[PDB]
Amino acid sequence: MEPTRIATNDRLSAAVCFDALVFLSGQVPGQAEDIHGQTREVLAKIDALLAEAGSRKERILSATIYLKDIARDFAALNEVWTQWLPTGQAPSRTTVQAELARPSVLVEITVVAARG
Amino acid sequence: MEPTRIATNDRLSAAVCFDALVFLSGQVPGQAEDIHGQTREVLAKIDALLAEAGSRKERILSATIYLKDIARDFAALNEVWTQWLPTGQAPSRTTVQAELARPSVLVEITVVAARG
Amino acid sequence: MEPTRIATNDRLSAAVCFDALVFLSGQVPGQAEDIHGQTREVLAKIDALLAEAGSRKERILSATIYLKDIARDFAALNEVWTQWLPTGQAPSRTTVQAELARPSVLVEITVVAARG
Image 1 (cartoon, rainbow over the protein chains, first blue to last red):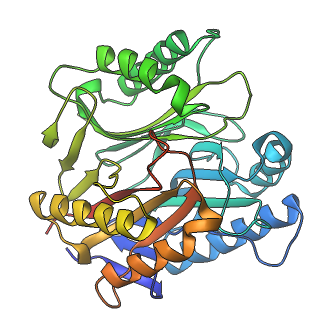
Image 2 (image 1 turned 60 degrees about the vertical axis):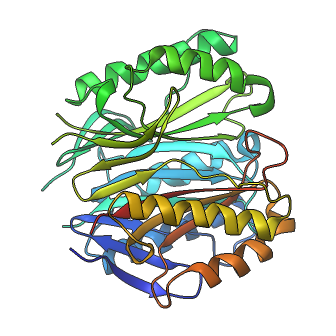
């Protein structure tokens, strides 16, 4: 009956759990400068937060994927994304263009998942 | 306790169901080139997925509506949207501008709904 | 087993409740023209809708924050946002750039929360 939080700072919590649902903050890349690397890094951060929250990649319910330049980077995003997903178990998905908080960030992904 | 999926490909599932919730992938138009036609087509695709997932238009919980050109197309979007909705039963809604994966796509809508 | 609605018009309901979840429509500012004022006003509108829906600021699960100009206004948004949040209880959050329905709107925030 109470939300619980993982990795809280003054602006956000990396994850909020409520009953059987896990809400992740939008994840941004690490040090990669290129789209492939950055997508890999975002997805790695998501996989770790899912684990910490009692979920897993197979239990993702929805992902919204924000690309700084969707025309330029959609193909690379899809390549890395499809490799990362568990086979036959893709979530619902929406991919749109949006500038992110820093101009060097090319990709940000926000996930909602089911706790196990 | 397990998500189920409808129309899964290598990138996404058109719908993911979990308990009493239905998460739809962002729906894009069919063959229409114009905003009115494209909005009608997106909403038709949503109505079919709601049916397949055990929901209905009256049970939509939230919609995020992405317009390639919000200044240009907000009025047309609203015309078609309000016609399509069941009377007195509009969902929560957010409408923002975002380029979609192809430049010819003017509108994309992502819905979360309650299973019946 | 049925969604309930708060403040329904022909396009949207300000809030939709379903079981223990509250889905708010994207909230836009009041009369403020500046980013600080507009953010304060959006957050005030959210706090009122949370109250009406049986929730509260401490029970927010996720927020998506849309900025017309993320480079310009991210710092001001964060200042007001962090002041408004209950201490140690920040939600999951995603902040991206998107033009809103009127050019004078600088900020719009969409919240999902847990009913108490």
